[PDB]
Protein backbone atom coordinates (compact mmCIF):
# COMPACT_ATOMS: atom_id res chain seq x y z
CA UNK A 1 0.00 0.00 0.00
CA UNK A 2 1.18 3.51 -0.87
CA UNK A 3 3.13 5.35 1.81
CA UNK A 4 1.51 8.62 2.85
CA UNK A 5 3.55 11.65 3.92
CA UNK A 6 2.66 14.33 6.45
CA UNK A 7 4.35 17.70 6.06
CA UNK A 8 6.09 19.04 9.16
CA UNK A 9 5.32 22.63 8.15
CA UNK A 10 8.97 23.11 7.19
CA UNK A 11 10.10 22.77 3.59
CA UNK A 12 13.66 22.17 4.82
CA UNK A 13 12.73 19.44 7.28
CA UNK A 14 10.34 17.87 4.75
CA UNK A 15 13.20 17.62 2.24
CA UNK A 16 15.44 15.92 4.81
CA UNK A 17 12.62 13.45 5.50
CA UNK A 18 12.02 12.72 1.81
CA UNK A 19 8.71 14.57 1.69
CA UNK A 20 7.47 14.35 5.26
CA UNK A 21 6.73 11.91 8.06
CA UNK A 22 5.75 8.52 6.62
CA UNK A 23 2.81 6.25 7.30
CA UNK A 24 3.71 2.58 7.87
CA UNK A 25 6.68 3.82 9.89
CA UNK A 26 7.77 4.95 13.34
CA UNK A 27 9.66 8.24 13.25
CA UNK A 28 11.55 9.06 16.43
CA UNK A 29 12.71 12.58 17.14
CA UNK A 30 15.06 13.08 20.06
CA UNK A 31 16.81 16.02 21.64
CA UNK A 32 16.97 18.19 24.74
CA UNK A 33 13.95 20.00 26.16
CA UNK A 34 13.09 22.85 23.81
CA UNK A 35 14.87 21.25 20.84
CA UNK A 36 11.57 21.38 18.92
CA UNK A 37 10.48 17.75 19.33
CA UNK A 38 7.22 18.55 21.14
CA UNK A 39 6.49 21.59 18.96
CA UNK A 40 6.87 19.31 15.94
CA UNK A 41 4.46 16.80 17.51
CA UNK A 42 1.84 19.51 18.00
CA UNK A 43 2.35 20.82 14.47
CA UNK A 44 1.99 17.36 12.93
CA UNK A 45 -1.25 16.83 14.86
CA UNK A 46 -2.64 19.77 12.88
CA UNK A 47 -0.92 19.11 9.53
CA UNK A 48 -2.24 15.54 9.28
CA UNK A 49 -5.78 16.96 9.13
CA UNK A 50 -5.11 18.96 5.96
CA UNK A 51 -5.82 17.66 2.45
CA UNK A 52 -2.84 16.14 0.62
CA UNK A 53 -2.17 19.19 -1.58
CA UNK A 54 -1.61 21.03 1.73
CA UNK A 55 0.66 18.29 3.10
CA UNK A 56 -1.86 16.29 5.13
CA UNK A 57 -3.77 13.01 4.90
CA UNK A 58 -7.33 14.18 5.56
CA UNK A 59 -6.95 12.40 8.88
CA UNK A 60 -7.20 12.74 12.63
CA UNK A 61 -4.56 12.35 15.31
CA UNK A 62 -4.08 10.60 18.62
CA UNK A 63 -1.69 11.96 21.24
CA UNK A 64 -0.33 9.93 24.15
CA UNK A 65 1.22 12.23 26.74
CA UNK A 66 3.59 10.82 29.39
CA UNK A 67 4.98 14.02 30.97
CA UNK A 68 2.16 16.58 30.59
CA UNK A 69 3.55 18.18 27.43
CA UNK A 70 0.22 18.46 25.57
CA UNK A 71 -1.03 22.03 25.14
CA UNK A 72 -4.52 22.32 23.61
CA UNK A 73 -4.19 26.09 23.14
CA UNK A 74 -0.97 25.57 21.19
CA UNK A 75 -2.90 23.32 18.79
CA UNK A 76 -5.61 25.97 18.54
CA UNK A 77 -3.01 28.67 17.82
CA UNK A 78 -1.30 26.63 15.10
CA UNK A 79 -4.70 25.87 13.56
CA UNK A 80 -5.93 29.47 13.62
CA UNK A 81 -2.72 30.77 12.04
CA UNK A 82 -2.92 28.22 9.22
CA UNK A 83 -6.48 29.28 8.33
CA UNK A 84 -8.21 26.44 10.18
CA UNK A 85 -10.94 26.42 12.82
CA UNK A 86 -9.15 25.90 16.15
CA UNK A 87 -11.99 24.01 17.85
CA UNK A 88 -12.58 21.59 14.97
CA UNK A 89 -8.85 20.87 14.76
CA UNK A 90 -8.59 20.31 18.52
CA UNK A 91 -11.57 17.92 18.37
CA UNK A 92 -9.67 15.85 15.79
CA UNK A 93 -6.82 15.21 18.24
CA UNK A 94 -7.70 12.44 20.67
CA UNK A 95 -5.68 13.05 23.82
CA UNK A 96 -4.74 10.53 26.51
CA UNK A 97 -2.40 10.82 29.48
CA UNK A 98 -0.31 7.72 30.20
CA UNK A 99 -0.03 7.30 33.97
CA UNK A 100 2.73 4.66 33.85
CA UNK A 101 4.38 2.33 31.33
CA UNK A 102 1.77 -0.40 31.77
CA UNK A 103 -1.08 2.04 31.21
CA UNK A 104 0.86 3.34 28.20
CA UNK A 105 0.70 -0.17 26.71
CA UNK A 106 -3.02 -0.43 27.38
CA UNK A 107 -3.54 2.94 25.66
CA UNK A 108 -1.97 1.53 22.49
CA UNK A 109 -4.52 -1.30 22.56
CA UNK A 110 -7.31 1.23 23.04
CA UNK A 111 -5.86 3.28 20.20
CA UNK A 112 -6.40 0.32 17.88
CA UNK A 113 -10.12 0.36 18.69
CA UNK A 114 -10.45 3.99 17.58
CA UNK A 115 -8.32 3.40 14.50
CA UNK A 116 -10.53 0.46 13.49
CA UNK A 117 -13.68 2.50 14.12
CA UNK A 118 -12.61 5.41 11.92
CA UNK A 119 -10.65 3.46 9.29
CA UNK A 120 -13.19 3.65 6.48
CA UNK A 121 -14.74 7.02 7.31
CA UNK A 122 -13.96 10.32 5.58
CA UNK A 123 -11.39 11.10 8.30
CA UNK A 124 -9.44 8.05 9.49
CA UNK A 125 -6.78 8.21 12.16
CA UNK A 126 -3.53 8.90 10.31
CA UNK A 127 -1.16 9.91 13.11
CA UNK A 128 -0.38 8.42 16.52
CA UNK A 129 1.97 10.47 18.70
CA UNK A 130 3.75 9.19 21.81
CA UNK A 131 5.56 12.07 23.50
CA UNK A 132 8.59 11.17 25.62
CA UNK A 133 7.92 7.49 24.85
CA UNK A 134 10.64 6.20 27.16
CA UNK A 135 10.01 8.38 30.22
CA UNK A 136 7.94 5.91 32.25
CA UNK A 137 10.12 2.98 31.19
CA UNK A 138 13.23 4.79 32.41
CA UNK A 139 11.58 5.70 35.72
CA UNK A 140 10.20 2.22 36.42
CA UNK A 141 12.93 -0.11 35.13
CA UNK A 142 16.04 0.99 36.96
CA UNK A 143 18.91 -0.72 38.74
CA UNK A 144 20.93 -3.90 38.38
CA UNK A 145 19.81 -5.91 35.36
CA UNK A 146 17.15 -3.36 34.42
CA UNK A 147 18.72 -2.71 31.01
CA UNK A 148 17.64 -6.04 29.52
CA UNK A 149 14.11 -5.85 30.92
CA UNK A 150 13.57 -2.21 29.98
CA UNK A 151 14.83 -2.79 26.44
CA UNK A 152 12.64 -5.88 26.04
CA UNK A 153 9.55 -3.99 27.21
CA UNK A 154 10.34 -1.05 24.94
CA UNK A 155 10.97 -3.39 22.01
CA UNK A 156 7.54 -4.97 22.54
CA UNK A 157 5.87 -1.57 22.85
CA UNK A 158 7.57 -0.46 19.64
CA UNK A 159 6.55 -3.71 17.89
CA UNK A 160 2.93 -2.99 18.86
CA UNK A 161 3.27 0.51 17.42
CA UNK A 162 4.90 -0.79 14.21
CA UNK A 163 1.95 -3.15 13.80
CA UNK A 164 -0.56 -0.28 14.02
CA UNK A 165 1.44 1.78 11.52
CA UNK A 166 1.68 -1.08 9.03
CA UNK A 167 -1.78 -2.61 9.48
CA UNK A 168 -3.77 0.63 9.40
CA UNK A 169 -1.50 2.82 7.25
CA UNK A 170 -0.79 5.44 9.91
CA UNK A 171 2.28 7.44 10.85
CA UNK A 172 3.62 6.83 14.34
CA UNK A 173 5.62 9.75 15.72
CA UNK A 174 7.51 9.41 19.00
CA UNK A 175 9.73 11.77 20.95
CA UNK A 176 12.50 11.15 23.45
CA UNK A 177 14.96 12.98 25.65
CA UNK A 178 18.64 12.56 24.82
CA UNK A 179 24.85 5.94 23.25
CA UNK A 180 25.01 2.13 23.00
CA UNK A 181 21.33 1.25 23.57
CA UNK A 182 19.40 -0.41 20.75
CA UNK A 183 16.57 1.45 19.02
CA UNK A 184 13.86 0.07 16.72
CA UNK A 185 12.19 3.16 15.25
CA UNK A 186 12.10 3.20 11.44
CA UNK A 187 13.80 6.59 11.28
CA UNK A 188 15.62 8.55 13.99
CA UNK A 189 16.03 12.32 13.85
CA UNK A 190 18.24 14.31 16.21
CA UNK A 191 17.10 17.87 16.95
CA UNK A 192 19.15 20.67 18.51
CA UNK A 193 19.09 24.44 18.94
CA UNK A 194 21.03 26.52 16.42
CA UNK A 195 21.72 30.19 15.84
CA UNK A 196 19.01 32.81 15.34
CA UNK A 197 16.43 30.79 17.25
CA UNK A 198 16.55 28.07 14.61
CA UNK A 199 16.42 24.35 15.27
CA UNK A 200 18.67 21.94 13.36
CA UNK A 201 17.66 18.40 12.32
CA UNK A 202 19.98 15.52 11.44
CA UNK A 203 19.08 11.97 10.44
CA UNK A 204 20.79 9.31 12.54
CA UNK A 205 21.97 5.97 11.14
CA UNK A 206 20.07 6.46 7.87
CA UNK A 207 22.43 5.53 5.00
CA UNK A 208 19.41 5.22 2.68
CA UNK A 209 18.62 8.95 2.75
CA UNK A 210 20.92 11.74 1.45
CA UNK A 211 23.45 13.66 3.56
CA UNK A 212 22.49 17.01 5.08
CA UNK A 213 20.83 18.91 7.91
CA UNK A 214 17.55 20.80 7.93
CA UNK A 215 16.93 24.17 9.57
CA UNK A 216 13.57 25.35 10.85
CA UNK A 217 11.84 27.82 13.15
CA UNK A 218 9.19 27.62 15.86
CA UNK A 219 6.49 30.20 15.14
CA UNK A 220 2.81 31.00 15.63
CA UNK A 221 2.19 28.42 12.86
CA UNK A 222 4.07 25.77 14.84
CA UNK A 223 6.98 24.66 12.68
CA UNK A 224 8.09 26.35 9.47
CA UNK A 225 11.33 27.32 7.73
O1 LIG B 1 -10.35 8.26 23.72
C1 LIG B 1 -9.88 7.15 23.41
O2 LIG B 1 -10.54 6.10 23.20
C2 LIG B 1 -8.38 7.04 23.28
C3 LIG B 1 -7.77 5.78 23.44
C4 LIG B 1 -6.41 5.62 23.31
C5 LIG B 1 -5.63 6.75 23.00
C6 LIG B 1 -4.24 6.96 22.76
C7 LIG B 1 -4.06 8.30 22.47
N1 LIG B 1 -5.29 8.95 22.52
C8 LIG B 1 -6.27 8.01 22.84
C9 LIG B 1 -7.66 8.16 22.99
CA1 LIG C 1 9.94 21.22 21.79
NA1 LIG D 1 6.89 -0.22 8.78
NA1 LIG E 1 -14.18 15.96 13.83
Image: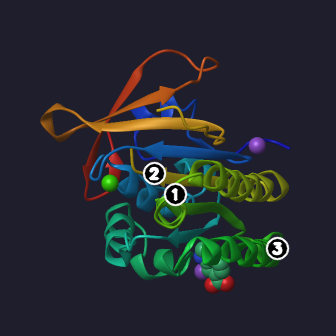
Task: Kindly report which numbered mark, 2 or 3, lies closer to the viewer in this rendering.
Answer: 2
Find residue 96 and report its horizontal and vertical position in percent. 54, 79
Q: Is residue 192 above or below residue 33?
A: above
Q: Is residue 42 above or below residue 3?
A: below
Residue at 64%, 19% in the rendered image: 208
Find residue 140 and report its horizontal and vertical position in percent. 52, 67
**Left or right, 114 with reference to 19:** right
The one nearer the camera, 66 or 43, is: 66
Q: Is residue 160 above or below residue 191?
A: below
The one nearer the camera, 152 or 142, is: 142
Identify the mark nearer the N-term, 1 or 3: 3
**Left or right, 70 with reference to 194:** right
Q: Is residue 7 visible?
A: no
Secondary element at image label 2:
strand
Residue at 46%, 32% in the rendered image: 179
Q: Residues within 10 Å of mark 2 (few under 14, many from 20)?
A: some
Residue under label 3: 116
Secondary element at image label 3:
helix
Q: Is ligand 2 less than 8 Å from the beta carbon at label 1?
A: no
Residue under label 2: 176
Q: Are marks 2 and 1 in contact (CB under 8 Å)?
A: yes
Q: Is residue 216 visible?
A: yes
Task: Kindly report which numbered mark, 1 or 3, lies closer to the viewer in this rendering.
Answer: 1
Q: Residues within 10 Å of mark 1 (few under 14, many from 20)?
A: some
Identify the mark nearer the N-term, 2 or 3: 3
Identify the mark nearer the N-term, 2 or 1: 1
Q: Is ligand 1 less than 8 Å from the beta carbon at label 3?
A: no
Q: Which mark is residue 158?
A: none
Residue under label 1: 134
Q: Quadrant of ligand 1?
A: bottom right
Question: Which image quadrant for residue 167?
Answer: bottom right
Residue at 80%, 41% in the rendered image: 2
Amino acid sequence: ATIGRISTGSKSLDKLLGGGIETQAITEVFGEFGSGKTQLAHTLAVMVQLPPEEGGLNGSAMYIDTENTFRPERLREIAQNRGLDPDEVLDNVAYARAFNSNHQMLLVQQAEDMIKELLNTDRPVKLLIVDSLTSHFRSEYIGRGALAERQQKLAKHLADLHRLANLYDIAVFVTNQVHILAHSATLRVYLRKGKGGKRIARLIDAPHLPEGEAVFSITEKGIED
